[PDB]
Amino acid sequence: XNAXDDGDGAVP
Amino acid sequence: XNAXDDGDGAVP
Amino acid sequence: XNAXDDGDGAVP
Amino acid sequence: XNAXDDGDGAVP
Amino acid sequence: XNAXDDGDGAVP
Amino acid sequence: XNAXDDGDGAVP
Amino acid sequence: XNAXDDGDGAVP
Amino acid sequence: XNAXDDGDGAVP
Amino acid sequence: XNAXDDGDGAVP
Amino acid sequence: XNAXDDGDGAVP
Amino acid sequence: XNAXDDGDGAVP
Amino acid sequence: XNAXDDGDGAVP
Ligand SMILES: CC(C)=CCC/C(C)=C/COP(=O)(O)O
Ligand SMILES: CC(C)=CCC/C(C)=C/COP(=O)(O)O
Ligand SMILES: CC(C)=CCC/C(C)=C/COP(=O)(O)O
Ligand SMILES: CC(C)=CCC/C(C)=C/COP(=O)(O)O
Ligand SMILES: CC(C)=CCC/C(C)=C/COP(=O)(O)O
Ligand SMILES: CC(C)=CCC/C(C)=C/COP(=O)(O)O
Ligand SMILES: CC(C)=CCC/C(C)=C/COP(=O)(O)O
Ligand SMILES: CC(C)=CCC/C(C)=C/COP(=O)(O)O
Ligand SMILES: CC(C)=CCC/C(C)=C/COP(=O)(O)O
Ligand SMILES: CC(C)=CCC/C(C)=C/COP(=O)(O)O
Ligand SMILES: CC(C)=CCC/C(C)=C/COP(=O)(O)O
Ligand SMILES: CC(C)=CCC/C(C)=C/COP(=O)(O)O
Ligand SMILES: [Ca+2]
Ligand SMILES: [Ca+2]
Ligand SMILES: [Ca+2]
Ligand SMILES: [Ca+2]
Ligand SMILES: [Ca+2]
Ligand SMILES: [Ca+2]
Ligand SMILES: [Ca+2]
Ligand SMILES: [Ca+2]
Ligand SMILES: [Ca+2]
Ligand SMILES: [Ca+2]
Ligand SMILES: [Ca+2]
Ligand SMILES: [Ca+2]
Ligand SMILES: [Ca+2]
Ligand SMILES: [Ca+2]
Ligand SMILES: [Ca+2]
Ligand SMILES: [Ca+2]
Ligand SMILES: [Ca+2]
Ligand SMILES: [Ca+2]
Ligand SMILES: [Ca+2]
Ligand SMILES: [Ca+2]
Ligand SMILES: [Ca+2]
Ligand SMILES: [Ca+2]
Ligand SMILES: [Ca+2]
Ligand SMILES: [Ca+2]
Ligand SMILES: [Ca+2]
Ligand SMILES: [Ca+2]
Ligand SMILES: [Ca+2]
Ligand SMILES: [Ca+2]
Ligand SMILES: [Ca+2]
Ligand SMILES: [Ca+2]
Ligand SMILES: [Ca+2]
Ligand SMILES: [Ca+2]
Ligand SMILES: [Ca+2]
Ligand SMILES: [Ca+2]
Ligand SMILES: [Ca+2]
Ligand SMILES: [Ca+2]
Ligand SMILES: [Ca+2]
Ligand SMILES: [Ca+2]
Ligand SMILES: [Ca+2]
Ligand SMILES: [Ca+2]
Ligand SMILES: [Ca+2]
Ligand SMILES: [Ca+2]
Ligand SMILES: [Cl-]
Ligand SMILES: [Cl-]
Ligand SMILES: [Cl-]
Ligand SMILES: [Cl-]
Ligand SMILES: [Cl-]
Ligand SMILES: [Cl-]
Ligand SMILES: [Cl-]
Ligand SMILES: [Cl-]
Ligand SMILES: [Cl-]
Ligand SMILES: [Cl-]
Ligand SMILES: [Cl-]
Ligand SMILES: [Cl-]
Ligand SMILES: [Cl-]
Ligand SMILES: [Cl-]
Ligand code: NA
């Protein structure tokens, strides 16, 4: 996997 | 963004 | 399956 | 807005 | 989960 | 939380 | 179709 | 489990 | 054909 | 992703 | 172990 | 894909 600090998908 | 051919999240 | 809006596992 | 105690999005 | 037609978070 | 005896996610 | 939350085959 | 006479997955 | 270990289509 | 002009899976 | 960001089995 | 002689997941 996750990127973005917003979990899976959304921001990479 | 998407990777994986499974849409957002899931497989990168 | 999924619950929680966070994908598989994590919050049910 | 927010729900979830996780801020905007994520868990409602 | 989402509301708003603008994805996760932002407008409910 | 978990269900399925396979841990978090996967089988509920 | 699928059952199981593990995709085609495996758990019904 | 299997259905279909094609093994696990595929036709139920 | 299949790729991905998830059968036909889905992940290549 | 897809190949084949027949969508996901089927002909690669 | 796991691979794929889909948990145990599924995509390696 | 599988490894381990125990099918998808579990032992790699
Ligand atoms: C090189 C590839 C193909 C991906 C690595 C980065 C990554 C793990 C993205 C997934 O982030 P999200 O789950 O937030 O979309
Ligand atoms: C290196 C980073 C940070 C991302 C590039 C690849 C990417 C855009 C992955 C996101 O895929 P999903 O939406 O399928 O998780
Ligand atoms: C009552 C049982 C046994 C399952 C129904 C609810 C469900 C489908 C949970 C899975 O959620 P996560 O994949 O987010 O853990
Ligand atoms: C009437 C609607 C549609 C929402 C009520 C609760 C709410 C404001 C949800 C948004 O929570 P997140 O920002 O955590 O997604
Ligand atoms: C049960 C609660 C508290 C809210 C349901 C409405 C909902 C699912 C809003 C989340 O929308 P966004 O992801 O657009 O913030
Ligand atoms: C009624 C609800 C909403 C959940 C109860 C069952 C549950 C806790 C599912 C989570 O299972 P996994 O963690 O294996 O996905
Ligand atoms: C009535 C029949 C015969 C099947 C209904 C259940 C079904 C659609 C199962 C296939 O699940 P898997 O793809 O997970 O093996
Ligand atoms: C009631 C359910 C849930 C399924 C019963 C029949 C079954 C065991 C389907 C699995 O067949 P495949 O392995 O061929 O997909
Ligand atoms: C380079 C081409 C054109 C195909 C070879 C690899 C292949 C056979 C992919 C099909 O996988 P799925 O059936 O999992 O989508
Ligand atoms: C690297 C691999 C293994 C595949 C690339 C070509 C491809 C993306 C085929 C998938 O096509 P279908 O979705 O039509 O099966
Ligand atoms: C040495 C071997 C044979 C495995 C290394 C990679 C691995 C740990 C695959 C298991 O991933 P899944 O649980 O997603 O299948
Ligand atoms: C390319 C990678 C990383 C793994 C190769 C070995 C493999 C396909 C293991 C998956 O085994 P299980 O389905 O038992 O987890
Ligand atoms: Ca991810
Ligand atoms: Ca993310
Ligand atoms: Ca994170
Ligand atoms: Ca999100
Ligand atoms: Ca994405
Ligand atoms: Ca895509
Ligand atoms: Ca993906
Ligand atoms: Ca699930
Ligand atoms: Ca979801
Ligand atoms: Ca969840
Ligand atoms: Ca909000
Ligand atoms: Ca808050
Ligand atoms: Ca936000
Ligand atoms: Ca929230
Ligand atoms: Ca949401
Ligand atoms: Ca929204
Ligand atoms: Ca939407
Ligand atoms: Ca759980
Ligand atoms: Ca357990
Ligand atoms: Ca489980
Ligand atoms: Ca099936
Ligand atoms: Ca499914
Ligand atoms: Ca499987
Ligand atoms: Ca299944
Ligand atoms: Ca079966
Ligand atoms: Ca059979
Ligand atoms: Ca079958
Ligand atoms: Ca195929
Ligand atoms: Ca296969
Ligand atoms: Ca595939
Ligand atoms: Ca495809
Ligand atoms: Ca096409
Ligand atoms: Ca195709
Ligand atoms: Ca097919
Ligand atoms: Ca594993
Ligand atoms: Ca993982
Ligand atoms: Ca999973
Ligand atoms: Ca497992
Ligand atoms: Ca996996
Ligand atoms: Ca496997
Ligand atoms: Ca085997
Ligand atoms: Ca195994
Ligand atoms: Cl992250
Ligand atoms: Cl993709
Ligand atoms: Cl959900
Ligand atoms: Cl909150
Ligand atoms: Cl919406
Ligand atoms: Cl988000
Ligand atoms: Cl359990
Ligand atoms: Cl399912
Ligand atoms: Cl059969
Ligand atoms: Cl495969
Ligand atoms: Cl195509
Ligand atoms: Cl992983
Ligand atoms: Cl094996
Ligand atoms: Cl599995
Ligand atoms: Na948005």
Image (cartoon, coloured by chain):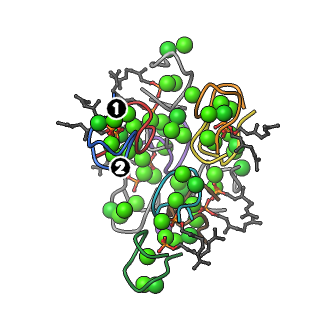
Chain colours: B brown, D purple, G red, H blue, I cyan, J green, K yellow, L orange
Q: Is residue K8 visible?
A: no
D6 with respect to L3 (left or right):
left
> Is the N terminus of chain J in the top left, top right, bottom left or bottom right quadrant?
bottom right
Name the residue type under label 2: Ala
**Cβ of mark 1 under 8 A from ligand 8:** yes
Q: Is mark 2 within 8 Å of ligand 39?
A: yes
Percent of width and height locating residue B2: 58, 68
- Label 1 Cα crowd, 10 Å radius (few <14 / some 14-19 / many 20+): some
G11 relative to J1, above or below: above
Q: Which mark is residue B4?
A: none
Q: Count up the numbered dots.
A: 2
Q: Secondary structure at mark 2?
A: loop
Q: Which residue is mark 1?
A: G12
- Establish if B6 lies above or below L11: below
The residue identified by callout 2 is: H10
Closer-to-camera residue (B2/D9):
B2
